[PDB]
Image: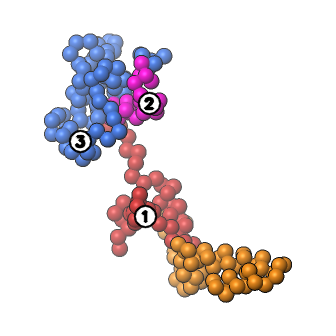
Amino acid sequence: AEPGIDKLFGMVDSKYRLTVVVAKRAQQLLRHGFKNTVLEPEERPKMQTLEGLFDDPNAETWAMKELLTGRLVFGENLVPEDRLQKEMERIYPGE
Amino acid sequence: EKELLEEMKHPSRARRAKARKRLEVVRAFLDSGNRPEWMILEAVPVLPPDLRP
Amino acid sequence: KGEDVPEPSVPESFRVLVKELQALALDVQTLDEKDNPVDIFEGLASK
């Protein structure tokens, strides 16, 4: 199976919640550049002839990975939906 | 409605069945329902063209 | 582009079943959380 899935079902009240979280994360992971991320420093996803999943193959895997850390925050109504997108586009370039 | 109310309860049985069924439709109209004069047409909508191309 | 995919707006089936329902003289209207009007037709409904 896929990396540490039991740990991710452990992270949420509904199985499906995980899916929604991951989905939306990969979404913004793509949309507002790819430097959205909280983890790049050293050893994050990778691929094989050069090496660069360190730029942009698979987004949701990145999501699962980040989420596997207590780095991200997920919750029913954390933040007002509009000022969210405002803030995302304002902080990160890459269009 | 009132006419049917009386028509329903007060006449003896074997009759008010149809008064019940009639009441249903009257209530239907006077509920969150509309006015029965549109039940007949004098304006016909035409379906768009690409749906009948 | 290299974008995700543009799922939403309105479904075909739905607008088509609205108008196709309207072709027989049925008034089929779409409502909000509170029973309010809702323009399914993408700002194209205007006369």
Q: Answer with mark 3 or mark 2, whichever residue precedes in sequence.
A: 2
Compared with residue A16, is residue B18 higher up or lower down, i.e. above or below? below
- From the image, state the color of chain A: blue
**Which segment did they paint magenta?**
A7-27
On the picture, is A39 further left or further right than C40?
left
Looking at the rendered structure, the kind of residue marked 3 is Leu
Q: Are marks 3 and 1 on the same chain?
A: no
State which mark lies toward you, 1 or 2: 2
**Place of residue C45 in the rendered image (x, y in percent of width and height, measured from the top left):** 38, 67
Disc 3 sits on a residue from what chain?
A
State which mark lies toward you, 3 or 1: 1
**Place of residue A57 in the rendered image (x, y in percent of width and height, measured from the top left):** 33, 23
Q: Which residue in the rendered view is the most extreme toward the front?
A: B10
**Place of residue B36 in the rendered image (x, y in percent of width and height, measured from the top left):** 58, 82
Mark 2 lies on residue? A13
Mark 3 lies on residue? A84
Mark 1 lies on residue? C35
Compared with residue C27, is residue A45 higher up or lower down, i.e. above or below? above
Q: Is residue A85 visible?
A: no
Task: Please state which of residues A9 and A31 is positioned toward the viewer in this rendering.
Answer: A9
- Quadrant in the rendering for residue A3: top left
Q: Residue at x 20, y 38 (%)?
A: A88
Dot 1 crowding, Cα within 10 Å, few <14, some 14–19, many 20+ = few
Chain in orange colour: B
